[PDB]
Length: 126
Ligand SMILES: CCn1c2c(c(=O)[nH]c1=O)[C@H]1C(=C(C)N2)C(=O)OCc2ccccc2OCCOc2cc(C)ccc21
Image (tube, rainbow, N blue to C red; front, side, top):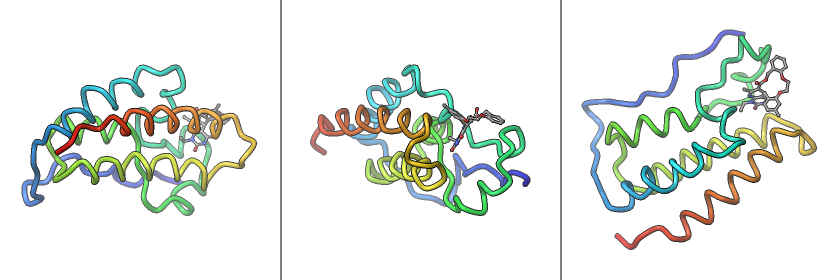
């Protein structure tokens, strides 16, 4: 029923790079999704207490959210663009695993995912 610690957004032992692709992921991709009308469920770690979801963190064992991603990008946490893309994909997949296919939140995630995949199709070359 309680929340786990959130995913780390810094770690002095983890290697990292600043690449043009990661800058794009922050300045274009994250910013575009963050401002979307459907972003709000995804802007912070899932609070299973507030949401009365005592099974959330029994079903979702790799939690991810755009607040964490935003901090990771701002903090230069990632080694490459693929690490960040994987975090977005985990976030969307978690929503589809936890929720039923007809749910409103699934429609919202699907709209954000469509936009996300459009923006990463324009991902600049390394
Ligand atoms: C991403 C994590 N997430 C998630 C929800 C969810 O259902 N599934 C998830 O995976 C919830 C939810 C959030 C922040 N996040 C929220 O704010 O819920 C308030 C709430 C509190 C107590 C009781 C019911 C209740 O709302 C029932 C409808 O829930 C909806 C419906 C829509 C359109 C969007 C989100 C949600």
